[PDB]
Image (cartoon, rainbow, N blue to C red):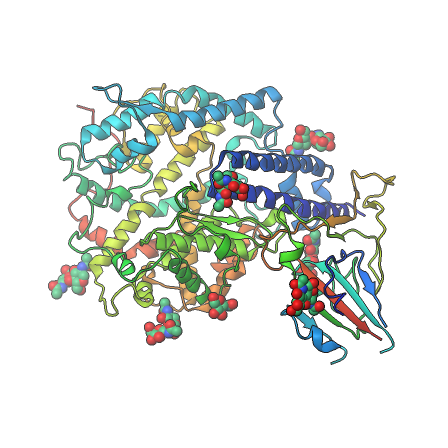
């Protein structure tokens, strides 16, 4: 666990890593863990999904939620049986002059079904005339960036999130 | 797909990009203001120019969505706030000329100076030295010299510039379907398409002229009292049935009568409440003040401070070399970054400015969830009114005696409350006729009802019959007396200062009814009551997403501004004045002039 919890670089929201490996009292012994909730329980395989999102969006990593994260980026099934933890990382993932290395998708033609990933980056068409792979009027680039900075109020600061799914 | 989905999809991207760019520009401007360096000026100007360029690009991009087929009111509000052209409908020639004359008027007002008749090498500016003479002097001849010279030396340079500023602004407004510039200015209070809360642009004039005819009975008694008190400091210069000379009113234009309090104090042997020694003997520093302000604000049910407010703010004057602009303001940088910039002393007026600025900060914190374009007060007069009611409620003896700055017994008498109410009326009531008259003159000048050969004539007749103030020297059509004021030569609207004074007392009288107050209104304190906090937060959290006629109703219960709460506030002073003017002549005559003999 000390490799998916200590990774020096985490993945963006729209392309989130999913680590599968073959001691729970160690994670329970660490930093304050701003959010820590597991709904179904207090296994054949374990899954560890990890990413970096904003503060006020940590409320969307939960079964039965809506928004721009639980719709287009990461959707959890309503029959969830894992446990989601999230902690602040303002002193690591935030830089003066912006940390534009973390992106997320805010335009998509359909919502995501649970545990699906989508990394394609074609131009989103909002109107009725074809776009032909070039931005402009009613054609948009679907991936935008967090402008993370240290002088941000909580809820607008970077939060590292790890979901541990159990079968 | 219809037209509305495309509008929402455009507004999402705009919201995100504009939020980021605005945060960058605001942080640059804060870094310049808190630490003055000439490289910070360039670091700020770069971000400012790039933000303005992004804004103009997105504005010319948002024109391709017709406003007559958007059916949502939020989307329509945002698109209509973004689609407006403002300037740039003029040619490059005319826009260049307009910017040139605006800059010229600004620098003429900023760097104009007058000097003595007996020593021409002693020239004084307006800011350090003219409004010091006009504020501290009791010499009739010195005040007359300053008043006349400021208008005859700077006021005569601004007339030929104003005469074409009027025309340029008028065609700029006509190019945007507004019929004049005054209508463009009144277009802030307009509400459309709500079917019950509407408000026209021509109804503001009627509602402003209707509320002023109820304030006249109090302003007339205040005028008579002030005149009968000035007849003892300037004998043989004031007539007991006439107007007041324009240079004896406390400042350069007569906008505030607050500097006449030393001459017209009711009972000079009862000192006003002033908790300054009790703070310095208890060693209150520049941060205990803000702790007390935050405690007062959380007492009524409002949230705490942001925990980033304490490290990033500037609550004390900076050190030896970090020269900064010391002007108490509240900054709303964005992304949850609220700050306060003021170089506080240990006084009683900084103790009130703290509450004012923290009320501003609480308002900014309330509507932080609205879209980027709907983050402002319901109109121009809501923000300062919300900031002012806190400073009103934080200066009552019931509050200071509970904080600990006054003795635990401190029996208060009625003479002290008369002193307090007169000091308040000299700055609250003494500025409503002036504001109303100035804005009426500007409206009529822009409309075309006053030909350019009758500006000074109409100005002084309106000053005589409305304000009750007479000029000490005849002024022909080569002067420009209004343009010698800051807001006129800098292109600012002046009606916000009128509606704010009414919204303030409406809010106060609506919140003192929820806190279960029983005595007079000028003694009310809303602290320790959560009903007032809830009633106010129900309005603070809306921003511009609702018409102002609905936000106003959420608190008060009416739809338009009323003037009865102000008279209910000043009733004891009104009774006392009515009893003091049994022998004087309440009113003035519009024929007496100081030079008429
Ligand atoms: C995460 O990694 C850091 C460093 O990569 C760990 O910090 C170490 O903590 C031990 C325990 O005292 C020290 O002996 C080491 O010197 C620390 N490392 C460094 C580089 O100073 C931290 O313990 C790790 N946390 C988890 C949960 O694995
Ligand atoms: C106020 O501004 C000045 C000028 O920008 C700053 O002075 C320099 O700041 C840079 C940025 O950290 C330093 O690398 C230099 O060593 C500073 N030089 C001098 C002579 O001061 C100054 O630091 C700013 N004030 C604060 C508190 O940061
Ligand atoms: C278009 O109008 C509708 C209602 O007229 C708005 O719907 C509201 O949306 C917010 C946030 O999604 C909800 O909290 C409200 O409950 C919705 N209203 C109702 C009555 O359910 C919608 O937001 C408007 N469009 C935009 C872009 O704001
Ligand atoms: C803003 O100014 C422009 C020109 O400066 C006005 O003209 C319209 O601009 C749009 C956007 O390019 C064109 O699609 C129209 O064909 C132009 N002519 C019209 C509408 O007659 C525009 O009307 C102005 N908008 C407002 C709200 O005043
Ligand atoms: C608001 O209410 C609180 C609590 O009722 C007041 O605080 C108490 O005031 C009494 C009387 O002055 C003291 O004996 C207590 O010691 C105080 N307790 C605390 C925790 O301060 C407070 O004075 C009230 N404030 C106002 C402005 O009425
Ligand atoms: C302040 O209150 C005192 C006490 O009520 C007032 O003194 C009385 O005033 C009335 C009015 O003329 C007299 O009839 C009484 O004889 C006065 N009392 C005494 C004991 O002589 C005083 O007038 C009030 N002052 C103001 C400005 O309202
Ligand atoms: C506000 O902060 C103080 C400490 O500064 C704390 O005692 C109080 O409980 C807080 N109130 C709220 C509503 O968070």
Image quadrant where one finds the C terminus of chain B: top left
Q: Is residue B342 above or below residue B523?
A: above
Q: Residue furthest bottom?
A: A42
B218 left or right of B158 in image: left
Locate residue B517, reporting x and y percent: 37, 67
Ligand 3 occupies quarter: bottom right
Q: As rendered, which of B273 and B552 lies closer to the eye?
A: B273
A57 left or right of B137 in image: right
At a point 13% along the width and 35% down the height, the residue shown is: B235
At a point 22% along the width and 54% down the height, the residue shown is: B576
At a point 34% along the width and 68% down the height, the residue shown is: B518
Residue A144 showing in the rendered view:
yes
Locate residue A11, reporting x and y percent: 77, 57
Q: Quadrant of residue B592?
A: top left
Q: Is residue B238 above or below residue B476?
A: below
Q: Quadrant of residue B66?
A: top right
Residue A64 showing in the rendered view:
no
Q: As rendered, which of B181 and B481 lies closer to the eye?
A: B481
Locate residue B380, reporting x and y percent: 49, 45
């Amino acid at each position: 666990f000390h490799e998916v919890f200590n990774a020096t670089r985490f993945a963006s929201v729209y392309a989130w890593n999913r680590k599968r490996i073959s001691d729970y009292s160690v994670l329970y012994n660490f930093a304050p863990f701003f959010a820590f909730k597991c709904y179904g329980v207090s296994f054949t395989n374990v899954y560890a999904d990890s990413f970096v999102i904003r503060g006020n969006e940590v409320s969307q990593i939960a079964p039965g939620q809506t928004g721009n994260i639980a719709d287009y980026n990461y959707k959890l099934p309503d029959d969830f049986t894992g446990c989601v933890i999230a902690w602040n990382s303002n002193k690591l993932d935030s830089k003066v002059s912006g940390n534009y290395n973390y992106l997320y998708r805010l335009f998509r033609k359909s919502k995501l079904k649970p545990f699906e990933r989508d990394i394609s980056t074609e131009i989103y068409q909002a109107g009725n005339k074809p776009c032909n792979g070039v931005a402009g009027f009613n054609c948009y680039f679907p991936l935008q960036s967090y402008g993370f900075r240290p002088t941000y109020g909580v809820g607008h600061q970077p939060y590292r999130v790890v979901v541990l799914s159990f079968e | 797909s219809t037209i509305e989905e495309q509008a929402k999809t455009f507004l999402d991207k705009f919201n995100h990009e504009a939020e980021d760019l605005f945060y960058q520009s605001s942080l640059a401007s804060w870094n310049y203001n808190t630490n003055i360096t000439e490289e910070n000026v360039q670091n700020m100007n770069n971000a400012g120019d790039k933000w303005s360029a992004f804004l103009k690009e997105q504005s010319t991009l948002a024109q391709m969505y017709p406003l007559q087929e958007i059916q949502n009111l939020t989307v329509k509000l945002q698109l209509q706030a973004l689609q407006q052209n403002g300037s740039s409908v003029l040619s490059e020639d005319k826009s260049k000329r307009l910017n040139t004359i605006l800059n010229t008027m600004s620098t003429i007002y900023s760097t104009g100076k007058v000097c003595n008749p007996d020593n021409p090498q002693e020239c004084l500016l307006l800011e350090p030295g003219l409004n010091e003479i006009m504020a501290n002097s009791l010499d009739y001849n010195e005040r007359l010299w300053a008043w006349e010279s400021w208008r005859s030396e700077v006021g005569k340079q601004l007339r030929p510039l104003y005469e074409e500023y009027v025309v340029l602004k008028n065609e700029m407004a006509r190019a945007n379907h507004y019929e004049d510039y005054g209508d463009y200015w009144r277009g802030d209070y307009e509400v459309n398409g709500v079917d019950g809360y509407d408000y026209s642009r021509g109804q503001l004039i009627e509602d402003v002229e209707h509320t002023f005819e109820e304030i006249k009975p109090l302003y007339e008694h205040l005028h008579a009292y002030v005149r009968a008190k000035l007849m003892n400091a300037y004998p043989s210069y004031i007539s007991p049935i006439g107007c007041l000379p324009a240079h004896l009113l406390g400042d350069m234009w007569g906008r505030f009568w607050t500097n006449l309090y030393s001459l017209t104090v009711p009972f000079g042997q009862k000192p006003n409440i002033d908790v300054t020694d009790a703070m310095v003997d208890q060693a209150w520093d520049a941060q205990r003040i803000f702790k007390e302000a935050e405690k007062f604000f959380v007492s009524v049910g409002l949230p705490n401070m942001t925990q980033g407010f304490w490290e990033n703010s500037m609550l004390t004057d900076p050190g030896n070399v970090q020269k900064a602009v010391c002007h108490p303001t509240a900054w709303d940088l964005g992304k949850g970054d609220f700050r306060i910039l003021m170089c506080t002393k240990v006084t009683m007026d900084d103790f009130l400015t703290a509450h004012h600025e923290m009320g501003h900060i609480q308002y900014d914190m309330a509507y932080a969830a609205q879209p980027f374009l709907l983050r402002n007060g319901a109109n121009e007069g809501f923000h300062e009114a919300v900031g002012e009611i806190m400073s009103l409620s934080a200066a009552t003896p019931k509050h200071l005696k509970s904080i600990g700055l006054l003795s635990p017994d401190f029996q208060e008498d009625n003479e002290t409350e008369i002193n307090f109410l007169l000091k308040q009326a000299l700055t609250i009531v003494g500025t409503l006729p002036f504001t109303y008259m100035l804005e009426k003159w500007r409206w009529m000048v822009f409309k075309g009802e006053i030909p350019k050969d009758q500006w000074m004539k109409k100005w002084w007749e309106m000053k005589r019959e409305i304000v009750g103030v007479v000029e000490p020297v005849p002024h022909d059509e080569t002067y420009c007396d209004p343009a010698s004021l800051f807001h006129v030569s800098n292109d600012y609207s002046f009606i916000r200062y009128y509606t704010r004074t009414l919204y303030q007392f409406q809010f106060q009288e609506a919140l003192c009814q929820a806190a279960k107050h029983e005595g007079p209104l000028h003694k009310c304190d809303i602290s320790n009551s959560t009903e007032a906090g809830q009633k106010l937060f129900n309005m603070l959290r809306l921003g511009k997403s609702e018409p102002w006629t609905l936000a106003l109703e959420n608190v008060v219960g009416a739809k338009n501004m009323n003037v009865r709460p102000l008279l209910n506030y000043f009733e004891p002073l009104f009774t006392w004045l009515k009893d003091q003017n049994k022998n004087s002549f309440v009113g003035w005559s519009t024929d007496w002039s100081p030079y008429a003999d």
